[PDB]
Length: 178
Ligand SMILES: [Zn+2]
Ligand SMILES: [Zn+2]
Ligand SMILES: [Zn+2]
Image 1 (cartoon, rainbow, N blue to C red):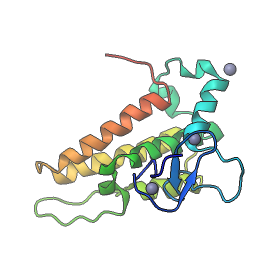
Image 2: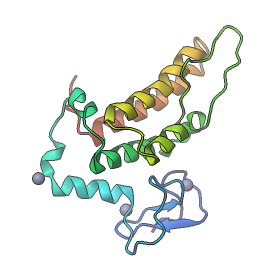
Image 3: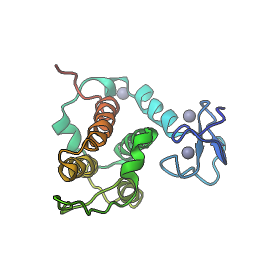
């Protein structure tokens, strides 16, 4: 196994996957690394199994169909994995915890949103469709772009949204387009 967390790239108290060489801090893995279970398989491994069991699940899909899917166990997992792929980028730090808004010439968003809030919402099974999860993720970046206006810091929101969107297209096998 690797000697650093796959998500945050630090050493520490690491749990090792049994079916691949990745390792995780307990609360870096999503869902949080399960108490017992030997062997244990990480989210990466679980997602690869879904694909292998249903190879056709990689054929292209329309986003509108994906968003309307109910949050059954496989869709729950895919959203957890997509959330985790965002936290894998170090720039996710800016969007992880609850924000506050006091900048001359801007007003804060009507509906603040942050990664740890989405993480809790997933854990508590608060989303009934993929659309709920995707809307909250996209709201994070949209709030950031609107608030920061012409400050160059707006770019961090574009950057992390691009990581989200690429991974959304991969994980949910969205049909490729120009
Ligand atoms: Zn970690
Ligand atoms: Zn694994
Ligand atoms: Zn099949």
